[PDB]
Image 1 (tube, rainbow, N blue to C red):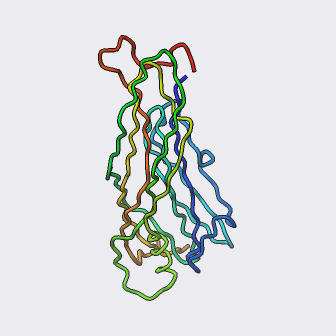
Image 2: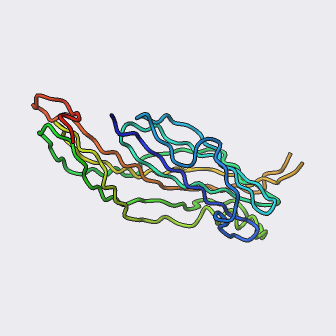
Image 3: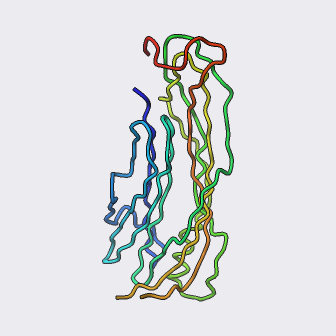
Length: 226
C-alpha cells in the first residue's frame, strides 16, 4: 500500500484595517477539505478557495495544490485579506523550482522495508518585489505589507519516511518560488483597481525516492514486510 502524497494549506487572515493577523478569531472555510489533502496515492493538482469572515468583513483567496506523486509532501500558506473597502485579487501566478537539494543514496538490498528519519529545512514566506501604489491610504498599505512579511527557514523532522525493500533510497527537497501579480480593487455593490503589486512567495516540497538499484534482481517493493 503506497505512501499517499500530502499537501497542507495554512490560511493566514489579515484584517487590513489594522494590519492584524486575526486568523484565530475569524470564521474560516475551505471550499473542499480541511486544509490537509492526501493522495490515493497521487494527488491531482486542484484549486481550493478559502473564505474568511470577521467583524462583518468577508474575503477569499485561492490556492493551487500541485500535482504530487506517491510520498511527496508539501505545504503552502495562503493570505486572506479582509477589508471593508477593498479586496486583493490575484491576477497571475507562476511557480518555478528555485533550488533542488538531493541527499546521497542508501541502498536497501534487503527484503524488508523500514521507516527512516528525514530532517529538512522548510523555506517559506513572502516578499513584495514591486509596488506601484503611490498613495497614503493606510488600509491599502496594510494589504500590501501583508504580502511582505519575509522569507523564513525552519527545521522540520519526519520520522516516518518509507525506505522500501530492494531500493536505492534518497530524498529531494525542492524550494519553489512563486511570482504572483495582485490588484487591489474597490469593493462596491464594478470597482476600480487602485493599486498593483508583485509578490515572490516560497514554499517547500519534499520527495523521498525509492529507485532501482542498478544491477539488483528486484525492483523496489515492501518485500517480506516491515
